[PDB]
Image: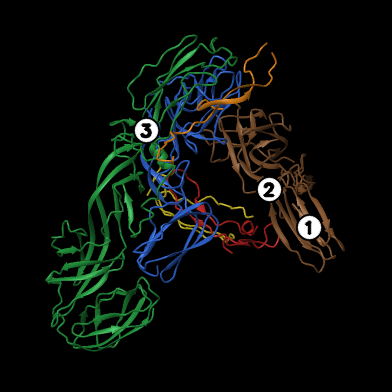
Chain colours: A brown, B blue, C orange, D green, E red, F yellow
Amino acid sequence: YKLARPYIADCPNCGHSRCDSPIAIEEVRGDAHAGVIRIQTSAMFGLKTDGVDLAYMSFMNGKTQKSIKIDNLHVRTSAPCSLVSHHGYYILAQCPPGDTVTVGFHDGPNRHTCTVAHKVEFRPVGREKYRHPPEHGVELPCNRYTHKRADVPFVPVKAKCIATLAPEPLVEHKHRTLILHLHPDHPTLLTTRSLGSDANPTRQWIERPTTVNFTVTGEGLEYTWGNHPPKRVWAQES
Amino acid sequence: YKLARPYIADCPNCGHSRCDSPIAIEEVRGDAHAGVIRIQTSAMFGLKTDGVDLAYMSFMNGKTQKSIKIDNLHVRTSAPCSLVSHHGYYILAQCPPGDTVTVGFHDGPNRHTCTVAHKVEFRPVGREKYRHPPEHGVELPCNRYTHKRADVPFVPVKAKCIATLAPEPLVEHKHRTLILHLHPDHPTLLTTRSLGSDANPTRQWIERPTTVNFTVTGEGLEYTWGNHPPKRVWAQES
Amino acid sequence: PPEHGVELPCNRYTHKRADVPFVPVKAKCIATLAPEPLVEHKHRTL
Amino acid sequence: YEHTAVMPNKVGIPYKALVERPGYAPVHLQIQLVNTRIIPSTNLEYITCKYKTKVPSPVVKCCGATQCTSKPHPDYQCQVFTGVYPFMWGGAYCFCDTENTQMSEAYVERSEECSIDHAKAYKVHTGTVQAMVNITYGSVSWRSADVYVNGETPAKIGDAKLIIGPLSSAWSPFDNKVVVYGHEVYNYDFPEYGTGKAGSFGDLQSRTSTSNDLYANTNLKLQRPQAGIVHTPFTQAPSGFERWKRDKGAPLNDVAPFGCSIALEPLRAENCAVGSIPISIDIPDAAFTRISETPTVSDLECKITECTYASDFGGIATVAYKSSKAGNCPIHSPSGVAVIKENDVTLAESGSFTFHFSTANIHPAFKLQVCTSAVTCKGDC
Amino acid sequence: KAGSFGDLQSRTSTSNDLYANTNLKLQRPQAGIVHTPFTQAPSGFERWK
Amino acid sequence: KYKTKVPSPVVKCCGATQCTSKPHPDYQCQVFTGVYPFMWGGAYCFCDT
């Protein structure tokens, strides 16, 4: 279950020259196409004085071992960030960048705050960004950590999050010609290739409303626009 | 000395309907060639009944007043900044621009935060900026401040500055040619010129592994990589 | 708007309670000034 | 006996030459110009640094007014500002949000923190150029003598009377007006002392680190607040130094066409590499070889065994000889496309002595001398 | 490869015959802070991306 | 992506430190002597030289 303890650990940046802080983020997992973070702190979350809550933590800042409400302890990147669940050494929170986490105390005497710039990143496994949910397109896999305890580590599990598919994918088929009328809001990768014995291998990154014409010989073509796996038309105007 | 008191000062935007506020930084000094800041704040940081402390402040207003221990009051640029010493009216901290400090308290009658960002422009005497001299790389003479406690102001101190350089300056010798295979971990300013009649006055900032060939007289060449005073090789296979 | 620089037209709202409702109006908003613009006059050329 | 030889300005390569007189053994002569320091006379025009704005506090009359009264400060500026507090914007503000008028006064001084943190405006007039020339005469390599590259003062030193005839080891990469940052010196021009503005270096002036000769033209523009008041707000032009920092030149330390390491606290150019340096060495005759190997040296061949292309001292060569008796006769390089590492050569009858040489060319052709016989060595670098 | 693809090598996601050549270059300690100062070449996988 | 692992640096106060090689993937060490002045960055040793 929870085999964690609240304690101080060294953090190279604190609010004073007093750097005897807890809340020092040992590890972070952010390898997802989500926005959520599993944080491993030296301070124990999911134990207050009374034990298990979803919105209280406990700490020893070398000047007071106590617990507080996540109010006095606010996560931030600058603006507040709200935790969701606690699993001992591990915190699970929503805090959109999820690679820059600053945990800091508005508790009682002295201001200990740790900030972490962990090596983990959110990234696409595709050719175009979908590393964080946009409002564009339709979903693709992400990782969102369990919001109940399931071993001290919160296990990473697959989940569904929004993904980029390029804005306004107006296709227009015509004779021997496939014009793709594009009207992105943001840098979208347009890749095309023929599916027949025709060629057209065209990668291009585009921004702003543009057109991109391709040959068709009556033997299909695929165009993926803004990170998709093959979308295909065949044996005509394709 | 340590005769400073808490008082108000005009802020551009602070809490309440008047910005004749607490925690408002009157003046800032960026008169270093390091990255360190001497701050003059109307509200006093760094003093409780102890004299010079690291973790208490006081402030007053008329509408949003009280004094606290530094905890609910966080200094930020958007991340922590650590004070080192207080000399009454003057605060001394390591903070990255050394001209922009945002102090705010998230307790009391309103939630006031003053930001100071008025000019006193500086950069190191080299060509790379620091927030305080790091361990990594070559030292350079510079100005900074006193950082030991001794209480009046923390006057400039001629003392070392340090510029980070990148990991591998692989020089490759040939006949009258020096290609510099450089492998940045971080943006390095590469300035070169050949030594001798031939010279190659070429400043460029590079990031990520690249090569850059320069002509050489046969009397040597200088390359400074990552802000240095000349790193030079002489007549040989240069 | 800061407090340093020339005041220029803007939309804004009243900033003290009238207890009437806060609704749009136009007020004055500070925008940054710049150093001296050194003009040099010459013949048919400025 | 004065012997004039020419050393390539390659700091670290000693230029071997022979002081040759027939019927006398050649003398080991190595001249290295180790360092050249171009030291110019610096006339300080002003110190310049970040200003500190001083606001004494503006005279504010709630429901009254005050007219400006001038006060003597370097960029004293006032403005009379009406309003202070906009109407309906405050919770214990002045009743008058119109009638209330503040006389907004402010000025600039030098900062208190310009104590060591300052840049320096220098007029630069013509210098002297020193050269640290390490001269070996015989086996006495243990004398090194300052000699001016400039004609100002030839070394009258006992080590050897040295003249370094002026060359590119002397110059001055320092223009008429020079900015010193405090570690990196940049040629940058600015108006002469008592004048400075934004669009050139300096516009706040001093002449010592703090105070003395306080002239400002920081273009202080008083402004009024939108809310609150304890001290009047302002916009300004940056300091001319601060402006200069946003409009930097190129630091001379890192760029300079002669291959000299411009170094700074006084601006000076250390360690040039340009050209080749005439060095006139008055050889001390007590170190002069002059049939001090009584052998006549005969039946020589030089074979260069290996060399690597134009290298520091990548030349490996072998000297065959017959000598009447073993001795040491000095080898040299009257060439500059090869310089010899050794200036001494082991006379023997073995037919092999391995000596090391240096190059800056892909062909090593130097003339090697024993006491009476001369040969040429050649190979491939 | 140093600062190029496969600067970390394995044969599964987790540790398994970890062979690296990440071009770790230790940096000389200087006054301002105490840590373990080094620079290193970029990750080869990331460089490859 | 690699994760850099930094084993805590072997500091010998008032003597020299000799690196002990470890067979970690791109293990590199360097011994640096006269590391810190103390009280201007930290040293945390009586000796400084």
On residue A122, the disc is: 2
On residue D113, the disc is: 3
Quadrant where the N terminus of chain A lies? top right
Q: Nearer the viewer, mark 3 or mark 1?
A: 1
Callout 3: 10 Å neighbours few (<14), some, many (20+)?
Answer: many
Q: Position of residue D195 (x, y in %)?
A: 32, 35
Q: Report which quarter residue D47 is drawn in.
A: top left
Q: Position of residue B20 (x, y in %)?
A: 52, 19
Type of amino acid at the residue the image marks with label 3: Glu
The residue nearer to you, when weighing A151 against A190, is: A190
Quote the CA–CA distance across marks 1 and 2.
26 Å
Q: Which residue is mark 1?
A: A223
Are dots 3 and 1 on a single chain?
no
Tag 2, which secondary structure? loop
Q: Report which quarter residue B73 is drawn in.
A: top right
A52 relative position to B16: left or right: right
Name the residue rendered at 49%, 50% in the picture: E37
Q: Report which quarter residue A162 is drawn in.
A: top right
Q: Is residue D300 above or below residue A188?
A: below
Specify the farthest residue to the right.
A235
Asked whether residue A109 is in view, the answer is no
Subunit of label 3? D
Type of amino acid at the residue the image marks with label 1: Tyr
Quadrant where the C terminus of chain A lies? bottom right
Q: Is residue D46 above or below residue B226?
A: above
Tag 3, which secondary structure? loop
